[PDB]
Image (tube, rainbow, N blue to C red):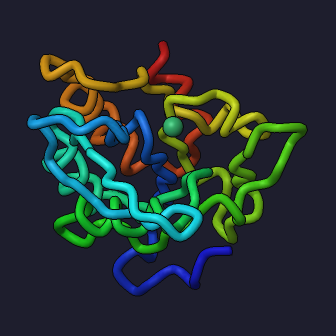
Amino acid sequence: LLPEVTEEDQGRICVVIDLDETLVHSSFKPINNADFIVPIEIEGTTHQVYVLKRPYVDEFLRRMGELFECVLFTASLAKYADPVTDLLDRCGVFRARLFRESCVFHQGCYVKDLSRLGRDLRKTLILDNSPASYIFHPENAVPVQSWFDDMADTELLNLIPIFEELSGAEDVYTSLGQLRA
Ligand SMILES: [Mg+2]
């Protein structure tokens, strides 16, 4: 599902990161406030999508790129997720981008089956505001609050030390256990 790990990612934990409401929040409603506007052609017609970036996402993503092998894994469709991530990931942090079709369908949910990834699950984390994405691996999860438009959010700032603590772990199940301890 994922390309072979690179030379530089060699010993790194693999962190799977969701897009909508975790890193960004999108809408069809025009706003003046928006960080990006992306044209998406819908059933062959063209819809402006207005995207707000979550506070600190740029610095959060940069640090993560220094510490982990970062993957984007979203249940949204590529035609949306690729341009939005292209503009969001202004430093090239994501090694891979997986979309709706790499998810499994579980009666109406799209689950991110971490075991299809080709990485040691003892060295994999998932960051996602929907517990339904991680039905099969809640023990690898680092939950995060949904975000929409709150400019005073500091959740990604709060989480940086957390991942800083985790980044050298040999088994995430032990580490998350001691973090929660
Ligand atoms: Mg989400």
User: Seen in the image, is 151 located left or right of residue 165?
Assistant: left
Can residue 155 be seen in the rendering of this structure? yes
Q: Which residue is drawn at 57% across and 60% down?
A: 77
- Looking at the picture, how far across and down is residue 59, in whole percent? 14, 47
For the N terminus, the quadrant is bottom right
- Looking at the picture, how far across and down is residue 122, in whole percent? 64, 50
Q: How many marks on residues?
A: 0
Q: Which residue is drawn at 83% across and 49% down?
A: 105
Q: Of all residues shown, which one is farthest toward the front?
A: 45
Q: Residue at x 39, y 40 (%)?
A: 166
Q: In which quarter of the image is residue 43?
A: bottom right
Can residue 66 be seen in the rendering of this structure? no
- Looking at the picture, how far across and down is residue 139, in whole percent? 67, 32
**32 vs 152: above or below:** below
Q: Quadrant of residue 101?
A: bottom right
Q: Of all residues shown, which one is farthest toward the left?
A: 32
Q: Of all residues shown, which one is farthest toward the top?
A: 181
User: Seen in the image, is 32 located left or right of residue 23?
Assistant: left
**45 vs 111: above or below:** below
User: Seen in the image, is 57 located left or right of residue 175?
Assistant: left
Q: Residue at x 70, y 64 (%)?
A: 102
Out of 152 and 135, give the one closest to the viewer. 152
- Looking at the picture, how far across and down is residue 143, in whole percent? 50, 26
Out of 162 and 20, give the one closest to the viewer. 20
**98 vs 148: above or below:** below
Out of 53 and 126, give the one closest to the viewer. 53
**95 vs 73: above or below:** below
